[PDB]
Image (cartoon, rainbow, N blue to C red):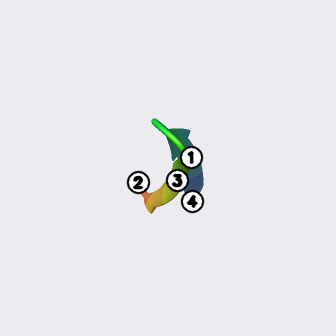
C-alpha cells in the first residue's frame, strides 16, 4: 500500500 510521508509516497 502507498501511504503519504513528507512530500512523497512510501510503500507500507
| Mark 2 in CB contact with mark 1 (< 8 angstroms) | yes
Which residue appears farthest toward the top when viewing the image? 6
At which x and y percent is residue 10? 44, 58
**Mark 3–mark 4 distance (CA, rounded to whole Å):** 13 Å
Residue 11 is left or right of residue 7, and the answer is: left
Mark found first going from the N terminus, 3 or 4: 4
**Mark 2–mark 3 distance (CA, rounded to whole Å):** 12 Å
**2 or 3: mark nearer the eye:** 3
Vertically, is 6 above or below 1? above
**1 or 4: mark nearer the eye:** 1
11 or 7, which lies in front? 7
Circle 1 residues within 10 Å: few <14, some 14–19, many ≥20:
few
Could you say which disc has been placed on residue 12 in the image?
2
**Mark 1–mark 4 distance (CA, rounded to whole Å):** 6 Å
Circle 3 residues within 10 Å: few <14, some 14–19, many ≥20:
few
Q: Which residue is mark 3?
A: 8
Residue occupying the point 46% across, 36% down: 6
7 or 12, which lies in front? 7
Residue occupying the point 54% across, 44% down: 7
Mark found first going from the N terminus, 4 or 2: 4
Q: Which residue is mark 4?
A: 1
| Mark 4 in CB contact with mark 2 (< 8 angstroms) | yes
| Mark 1 in CB contact with mark 4 (< 8 angstroms) | yes
Query: Which secondary structure, mark 4?
Result: loop
Q: Which residue is mark 1?
A: 3
At which x and y percent is residue 11? 44, 63
Amino acid at each position: 500500500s502507498w501511504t503519504w510521508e513528507n512530500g512523497k509516497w512510501t510503500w507500507k
